[PDB]
Image (cartoon, grey):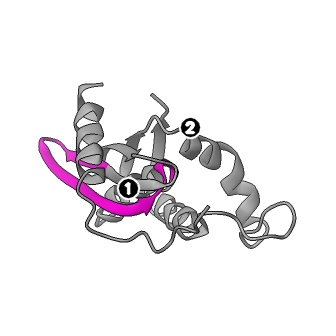
Amino acid sequence: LKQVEIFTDGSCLGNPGPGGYGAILRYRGREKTFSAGYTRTTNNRMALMAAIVALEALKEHCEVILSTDSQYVRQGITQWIHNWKARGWKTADKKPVKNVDLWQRLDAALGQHQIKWEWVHPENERCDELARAAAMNPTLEDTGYQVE
């Protein structure tokens, strides 16, 4: 299957506050760029978005090496995402899980490809800049964010 590399990064001026994401999809040379800024969001939601958008842009089952420094994403993937699904997406108290709208989208995207996560670079530097640039020029509302 096609081999591709994805780089991502989220950024937020507050918690919550204006934020943005930056992601890069690379296929043997070619490179696709993604970024958007939201008026009020969190670094966590932006970190997920960056991964979600790049992955959903894929049009076939791919072998993906996904790089992200978000420890929030790292946890969900290596720990929470498993339990959540085995409970109809609910916390330990049968209560809804935060950012379920994004975690579900990320979970769906993961089921589409064979993902190898790199929890760690010149490539990620651009994403950081795209994300910061988006956070400084928000153009959309992050409806999925539940205030406070």
Q: Which badge, 2 or 1, comes first in the chain's sequence?
A: 1
From the image, state whether disc 2 or disc 1 is nearer to you.
1
Side of 11 relative to 145 (left or right): left
Determine the CA span between mark 2 and mark 1: 20 Å
Name the amino acid type tagged 1: Pro
Name the amino acid type tagged 2: Gln
Tell me which corner region of the image, top left, top right, bottom left or bottom right, holds residue 147.
bottom right
Furthest residue toward left: 29
Element carrying mark 1: strand
Q: Residue at x 15, y 47 (%)?
A: 31
Element carrying mark 2: helix
Residues drawn in magenta: 22-44
- Which residue occupies the foreground of this view, 25 or 99? 99
Task: Look at the picture and state if 56 lies above or below 22.
Answer: below
Give the residue number, with chain letter if any, for mark 1.
Answer: 18
Q: Residue at x 58, y 69 (%)?
A: 146
Give the residue number, with chain letter if any, for mark 2.
Answer: 71
Side of 116 relative to 125 (left or right): right
Residue 8 x, y percent position in the rendering:
35, 44
- Which residue occupies the foreground of this view, 43 or 72? 43
- Which residue occupies the foreground of this view, 125 or 62? 125
Q: Residue at x 50, y 58 (%)?
A: 110
Furthest residue toward right: 93
Residue 61 x, y percent position in the rendering:
37, 61
Quadrant containing the C terminus in the rendered view: bottom right
Task: Look at the picture and state if 115 lies above or below 94.
Answer: above
Residue 74 x, y percent position in the rendering:
57, 41
Task: Look at the picture and state if 29 lies above or below 144.
Answer: above
Task: Look at the picture and state if 123 lies above or below 57.
Answer: above
